[PDB]
Length: 116
Length: 116
Ligand SMILES: *[C@@H]1O[C@H](CO)[C@@H](O)[C@H](O)[C@H]1NC(C)=O
Ligand SMILES: *[C@@H]1O[C@H](CO)[C@@H](O)[C@H](O)[C@H]1NC(C)=O
Ligand SMILES: *[C@@H]1O[C@H](CO)[C@@H](O)[C@H](O)[C@H]1NC(C)=O
Image (cartoon, rainbow over the protein chains, first blue to last red):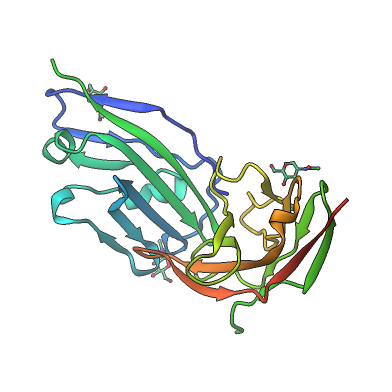
């Protein structure tokens, strides 16, 4: 497996212009991003994917702001970034799934919105 | 270069009830990118027995250190065998996608269970 440095939850308020949902693999050994695949899932849907072999990111139109920083994958960082509009209407549990060659793993993080 | 092979060297395995079963599988390549999974049976009603995701298969783990990038051994151990576990077990390579697709199957290993 790919193993994760786990986080139970992250929180944001009206004050956040964007949000980050952390995802960190602790035993990544990738030499090139072509070897890597990432899926972020919400309520059973793939709301962000990165197919390294094609250098291709894919999001649905209701998560149009979702992205990762592809350059950080080789360090094991697959953290999701989105704008506050996509975030405030889609609070809940996010699954980060990473694959490197044949090794795979996933971790879950709850995105929580605090009303102030 | 040669095609990826999924090799299940044993056509059959016999286990005494209560013992652990070892089902062998190796791959000859780690690309194309995608996981290995084990099933009992084939076709649309087959049962997922193992993949590398943490906390899903309390009876099943890999024999070798499959947390290493270079690992090509996907052999598994299943604890506490009962007659209910008898069947044909397949080691299956997938390619990544939305959703993942079956790429190549091993030949299958028939597990027979010996009562009392
Ligand atoms: C929201 O902003 C705060 C304050 O800068 C920060 O600490 C927190 O990590 C942000 N939350 C998310 C989910 O990005
Ligand atoms: C990763 O591999 C691809 C395919 O060979 C290549 O085009 C790309 O430039 C490589 N990355 C770097 C930083 O060289
Ligand atoms: C110990 O547990 C693992 C599953 O984590 C299982 O595959 C293995 O067979 C067990 N060992 C014995 C001796 O029962």
